[PDB]
Image 1 (tube, rainbow, N blue to C red):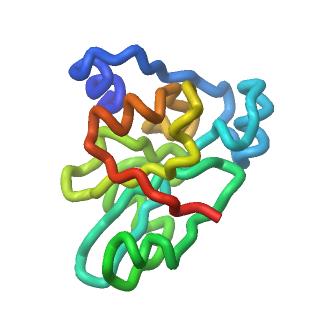
Image 2: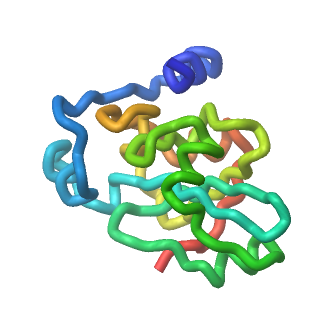
Length: 150
């Protein structure tokens, strides 16, 4: 609901696609949509050691470059554990969206995604994928573009 309401409020053309059964891996999501893993993006929650929380969107075929986030944050960082992801965002582990998150969370988008017109991220539920444009996401949120994947 929150993700759909967010899209409508910004007047964007993004859509929620529904998987009959939730996917368990990035490979499965890419295959079912007929795209590549790099087009299935994950919203990773990252925590610094002073209460800071970040949502970092990266290609599905990469992993977070921790050192890069430490440099961006300017403080020691780590990945939020699964229970922390749910607690701090209000969304399920496999459905964390890149928008409509609590306002304290800082959004970071990996620049390798910017040339892609369409990607599929967390839709707010384990079985929903958000079809969106990385550039539109950045423009709408003021997100920080960085090199945070490896």
